[PDB]
Length: 313
Length: 126
Length: 56
RNA sequence: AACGAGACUCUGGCAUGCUAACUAGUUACGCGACCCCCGAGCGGUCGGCGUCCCCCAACUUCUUAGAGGGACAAGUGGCGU
Ligand SMILES: [Mg+2]
Ligand SMILES: [Mg+2]
Ligand SMILES: [Mg+2]
Ligand SMILES: [Mg+2]
Ligand SMILES: [Mg+2]
Image (tube, rainbow over all chains, first blue to last red):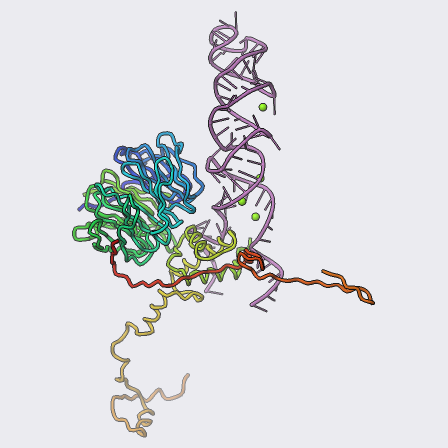
């Protein structure tokens, strides 16, 4: 029985951890963005003494850091912030070499092209925006778009047809046709605003979630609601596994993992008992990201910690 | 210090929750943005205090109902408990039995079944 | 404020008027009174929803 | 329901984030010049002192002043019908 166990904890932050990034070129490096205006590049000494140490602390931002994603080669980081800007760092020195300016309001998420030639972002402005790596705004989808905050957009690692998926607060999913930027299809349902959306490595699914508490699956060429997984309280962020047919979801206080063959819980990852005197005793989980290995996941919580979980038999 | 919110801060925060309840989560910095979008608060200082009472009220409403806010999702669970209760499919039954001075109250109204008898301890209460 | 001369000394006049919040206009001022929060609310939210998927 | 209280307006405290500056600068060197060996060196070079002179160099940390951001009893623990 493939079962997750608490491997170790990472510590050193000063606010909520809101995103974690990983890349196969470097297995010892991990990038975590936070709610204290800074992002942290770690140095994973896998010794159980402390599973890691903060290597470098990138700075320069005026508000919360909502999203972060590494380049395809592991040398550039792109981060998007509530101050309404994106910064393209340089994960050797620091020194943001390029920055992007135009969203009127908080940037809620950003995504990177697998050939590192297009950048997409969505915002409280109610708009999707597409950019060159020189920071010129290439296109703005103000029409045809959501009517509320564009909470998360993603790039499809598809073979040839370039399409981007979007999930917002008007409780819709919208798939786009690149090179013409018209709405391919919609996906309706989802009573409650939406928090994330994420596609499988090959691209056939979009495990989306939100206030409904449930994770819906969708089809990328057929265009049907495949099925719903019932999650419980609320779904902060969802992620497919790199090397298996698994989906992991971060429910409120605890993580849930599903096998899609027969649509069944593998396990719920909890945390330990505490003597806290209150409603919402658990710090909630915010965002989680598999490794490139497929042998460990990190998940960031609302108590300034990043916890590491490892698979065992 | 003080920190006693005025009635113009405790009435915004009451209307807002009624209208927009499904946006107002449980953290302060997201509410500080939702409130800024939905209503027109003509100051930063007032906006923050309104969005700071909204969070108090939200934490309280994730327990039992509060007596100033009528939200849709919490009416129906009371409407249920008024439509019927989980206790019985029978009535509380007609098959119930009583004691003297009522047998003669019925003897002058003509009943004849399903009763009992016990002449009570022989002087008034003590 | 004004003065008035009558054959028995002077009277004074004071008049104060409160302008009625002309939005963007010229009859009164913009920028309503500070303690004037106002909440807007739309409709047409029909929740009836089974996961249908339109295609363009 | 109205006024007063409060909200409000100015000011003080924080931004190595933005806007941008020979009527504010800094760092660099293009400099060069003065002076001392004051240290490697010798005295130059390596360096040290400069409200000494420059740049059609790079930038905005210090200066100036505009737009936004930030604090809410918001988080955690007690006392509160
Ligand atoms: Mg003040
Ligand atoms: Mg000052
Ligand atoms: Mg000087
Ligand atoms: Mg200001
Ligand atoms: Mg308390």
